[PDB]
Image (cartoon, grey):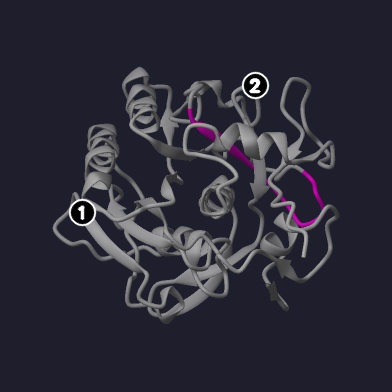
Amino acid sequence: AAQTNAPWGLARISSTSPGTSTYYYDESAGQGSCVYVIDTGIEASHPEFEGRAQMVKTYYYSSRDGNGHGTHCAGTVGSRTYGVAKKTQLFGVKVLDDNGSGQYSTIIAGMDFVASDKNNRNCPKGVVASLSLGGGYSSSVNSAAARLQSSGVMVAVAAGNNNADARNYSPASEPSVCTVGASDRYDRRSSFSNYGSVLDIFGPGTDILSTWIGGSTRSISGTSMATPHVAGLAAYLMTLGKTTAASACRYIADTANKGDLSNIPFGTVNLLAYNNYQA
């Protein structure tokens, strides 16, 4: 399948070179997989989700995304126009309030919730979790992410936007989950993107067009934006039978565009998420 005039990030993950505008992908599109978007919520109403998005848990007095961040992230995972895995099932877990903040105790509970709730759901091709969130180093937060991964979920987390070593951030610094840095449309490291040995992969993170609340769209930047590219790619690849939740991060690194990014500090991987789709 091919999507004409796709957002640059989607075109990027189906090309070996930057600058293209078509997203090439296998028509299975992540059907039969599920991605949990652990964030500010999802506006499931949005026509771009085509009924494939639903809230399953909230930690605040409402399950509505009053911010947009979570809806944007979910759109990059799985919306019809802006999504990597256009047929995946999307589950919203609202651990962040409408200012985009949340306590670590709440984020940990949300991760534990997904580890159990996936046993309530029909996800025959496997389960992914996208965590476009983080703060300072926490062993408890790292352990929660490691438990979610161990339970059989492919966990992708944002490296952070501090232009610093992600070793000092959580859950970015957890070794067993997939930590995602951000690049821009010219294959430069995004100016805000964290770096360091704990990063596993880069994804498109600067000027990413996706869904927004109120049935609209907008372009924003962050390692928050790169993480759902990788989470969606994982769901796409698990549907194709090419990998599993336990191995997807390594498989994505195995098959990444290698050495294409500039301003990568010494000791940080130079790998860019890539679907290697051959029509």
- Above or below — where is 269 with respect to 101? above
- For residue 194, say whether it is visible: no
> Secondary structure beneath disc 1?
strand
- Disc 2 residue type? Ser
Which residue is disc 2 drawn over?
197
Task: Give coordinates of residue 259: x percent, y percent.
Answer: 84, 36
Task: Give coordinates of residue 135: x percent, y percent.
Answer: 42, 33
Task: Give coordinates of residue 206: x percent, y percent.
Answer: 66, 55
Task: Give coordinates of residue 183: x percent, y percent.
Answer: 71, 47
Q: Which residues are magenta?
A: 177-188
Is 210 on the left or on the right of 20, as rendered? left
Is 260 on the left or on the right of 147, as rendered? right
The picture quadrant where one finds residue 7 is: bottom right
The picture quadrant where one finds residue 269 is: top right
Outermost residue toward the left in this view? 61
Question: Which label was assigned to residue 58?
Answer: 1
- Above or below — where is 119 with respect to 195? below
Query: Does residue 181 belong to the magenta stretch?
Result: yes
Relative depth, front residue between 210 and 52: 52
Label 2 vs 1, first from the N-terminus:
1
- Above or below — where is 11 with respect to 175? below
Residue drawn where x is 46% and y is 46% of the image: 132
